[PDB]
């Protein structure tokens, strides 16, 4: 129907929002990786303190 | 009705294309013309009018 000059049927808008969903998933995964790094770090301290 | 080929991965990485040829593709002002510049491709004057 039209090129990227509508923002609701535009191609650019489409591709943008898909890429943003990707950025939200990627962000979430990134956070979780950080969190389990935090956890592991702690577990080292927990076991140490336990000794 | 311009033609948008996607060319790159991201937004706007694209081009435009157009085309026109048919029977009425003789000399084009904005339309072809009236009694001239349309028939010359479509209907030749080579009926008798050269005589």
Image (spheres, coloured by chain):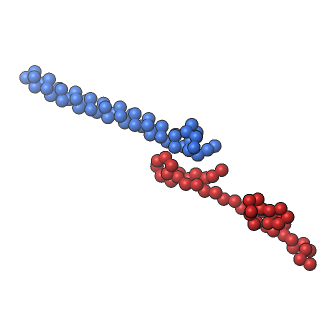
Residue at image location 30% in from the left, 30% down from the top: A32
Residue at image location 54% in from the left, 43% down from the top: A11
Residue that sits furthest to the left in the current view:
A51
Q: Quadrant of residue B31?
A: bottom right
Residue at image location 84% in from the left, 70% down from the top: B44
Left or right? Give the position of A31 relative to A21: left
In the rendering, at what x and y percent does residue A44 appear?
15, 28
Left or right? Give the position of B33 relative to A8: right
Residue at image location 83% in from the left, 62% down from the top: B34
Residue that sits furthest to the top in the current view:
A50
- Nearer to the camera, B15 or A51: B15
Q: Which chain is red?
A: B
In the rendering, at what x and y percent does residue A1 appear?
63, 43
In the rendering, at what x and y percent does residue B14 appear?
52, 52
Residue that sits furthest to the front in the current view:
B29
Left or right? Give the position of A1 relative to B43: left
In the rendered image, the vertical position of residue A40 relative to residue B21, given as above or below:
above
In the rendering, at what x and y percent does residue B27 appear?
75, 66
- Nearer to the camera, B37 or A1: B37
- Nearer to the camera, A28 or A17: A17
Name chain A's colour: blue
């Amino acid at each position: 129907d039209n090129a990227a000059d509508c923002a609701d049927i535009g191609f650019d808008a489409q591709l943008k929002v898909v890429d943003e969903a990707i950025n939200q998933v990627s962000s979430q995964r990134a956070k979780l990786g950080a969190v389990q790094n935090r956890l592991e770090h702690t577990i080292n301290n927990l076991s140490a303190s336990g000794e | 009705k311009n033609l948008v080929f996607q060319i790159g991965a991201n937004a706007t990485q694209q081009i435009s294309v157009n085309i026109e040829d048919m029977g009425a593709d003789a000399l084009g002002i904005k339309e072809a013309d009236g009694s001239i510049a349309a028939l010359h491709s479509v209907n030749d004057l080579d009926v008798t009018k050269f005589a």
